[PDB]
Amino acid sequence: MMASVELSADVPISPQDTWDHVSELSELGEWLVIHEGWRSLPLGAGVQIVGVARAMGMRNRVTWRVTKWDPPHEVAMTGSGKGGTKYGVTLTVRPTKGGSALGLRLELGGRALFGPLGSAAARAVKGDVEKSLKQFAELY
Amino acid sequence: MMASVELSADVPISPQDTWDHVSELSELGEWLVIHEGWRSLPLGAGVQIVGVARAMGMRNRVTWRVTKWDPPHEVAMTGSGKGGTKYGVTLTVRPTKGGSALGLRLELGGRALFGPLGSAAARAVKGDVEKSLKQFAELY
């Protein structure tokens, strides 16, 4: 189970400059709240690097992997955490009047959201889905 | 903020029969764990109907609206709750050997997940995203 928040903001620079800035992963710690800094750095998909992630006051060492790299449209990475917590950061660049639109999607798992007990929540809803699929099979 | 769980199960009936079963919304209470029954019923997109939703032991009266209706592939509805809680049910039908694959995606908001205080969690992460977008604007 993953919970996502997606927010977009407009910036008066070219989609070129915006992409070149967000694609500068070394500078990610300058402005992305949840990235405190790296602990490992080449760039493209499959690149694996360890960083420190600050979410919800919990700080956790995460192994990030670039899952998508589409210049100059968008870059997306997912990461694994110590407690099996899952993270996702998806930055998109679109054109707009006056410049660009930068969209950040933040994805957190249950454990990264609430601790090792948000897994209780995740398990409950996953079991609801499992039971629904079964009852469907058993009735048709 | 919305948290999603998506699980797929295989059923030995034709994609025809599977779609006709999941599209029978009156029978949704037969097998979908979170749908306890309706309180209102025509069918297609924009159709608005009130039902009772059981998620996480919390029972809440939800105004569901069919947001997507694609025979015989998939049907998707989102719903509003008393506390401003948000719900989403997305049932997809694909073909496979031996019959069909039925996929259920369940989407719950923070309040429907944890009560009026999961909104604290949602607000925290939404504010992280807002701050990140701002700091980006202020630095480029």
Image (cartoon, coloured by chain):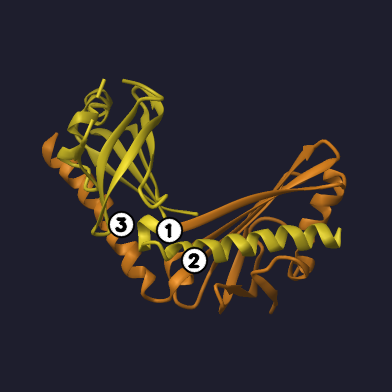
Chain colours: A orange, B yellow
Which chain does the numbered disc 3 sit on?
A: A
Residue B136 vs residue B117: left or right? right
Q: Residue furthest left?
A: A139
Residue A66 in the image, given as x and y percentages of width and height? 64, 59
Q: Earlier in the sequence, mark 1 or mark 2?
A: 1
Residue that mark 2 sits on = B121
Which chain does the numbered disc 2 sit on?
A: B
Residue B42 in the image, given as x and y percentages of width and height? 26, 20
- What secondary structure is marked by label 1? helix
Q: Quadrant of residue B37?
A: top left
Seen from the viewer's position, the closer of residues B125 and A91 is B125
Q: Are marks 1 and 2 in contact (CB under 8 Å)?
A: yes
Dividing the image into 4 quarters, which one contains the C terminus of chain A? top left
Residue that mark 1 sits on = B110
Residue B14 in the image, given as x and y percentages of width and height? 23, 26
Real-space CA distance between mark 2 and mark 3, rounded to the nearest whole angstrom: 20 Å
- Same chain assignment for discs 3 and 1: no
Q: Residue furthest front?
A: B82
Dividing the image into 4 quarters, which one contains the N terminus of chain A? bottom left
Residue A33 in the image: above or below residue A103: below
Residue found 77% across the figure and 57% down from its top: A22
Q: Are marks 2 and 3 in contact (CB under 8 Å)?
A: no
Real-space CA distance between mark 1 and mark 2, rounded to the nearest whole angstrom: 7 Å
Residue that mark 3 sits on = A126
